[PDB]
Length: 73
Length: 73
Image (tube, rainbow over all chains, first blue to last red; front, side):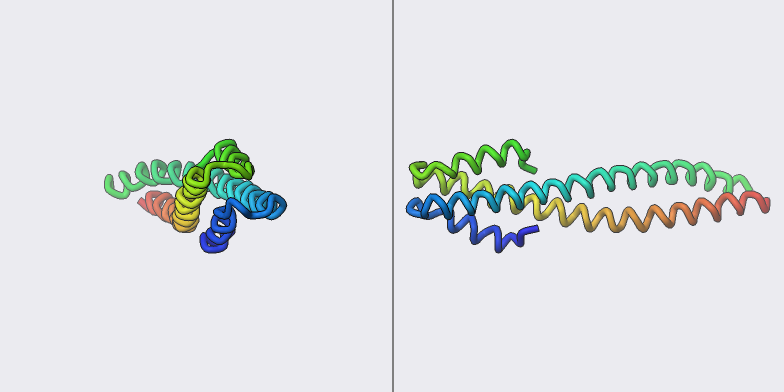
C-alpha cells in the first residue's frame, strides 16, 4: 500500500550511515509491516483470481460445447 | 516478488550500523527494484481480476442463452 514515493523516502532515510539506531530501526520496522501487509493483500487477490479463473475455464469449455450445437442446427 | 523470508533478510542486514556504506546502498536498491515490480504485478493483477470478473459473468449469461437456444431447436 505504501506509494512507491513514500516507500522511496524511507529507502532514502536508511542511506545515512550516521542515522540514529533508534530511527533506522523504526524505518526498517515500517518497511517490514508494510511489506507484510502488501504480500498479504497480493496473496488474496492471487487466490481469489485463481478461483475466478477456474470458473471461467469451466464456462469456456461448457459454452464451446454448446456453441458447437448452435452450428449443428 | 521477493519472498517474505528474502525481504526479512535484507531488513536485518540493513539494521547493522556498521554495514559497508557501498553495500547498504546496494541492498537498499533491491528494496526499490523489488518494490517497483511488486507495485506493478499488483496493479496488473487488479487490472486483470477486474476484467476476469466481468468476463465470468458474461460467460454465465452466454451459457444461459446458448442452452435455452438449443432447446428451441
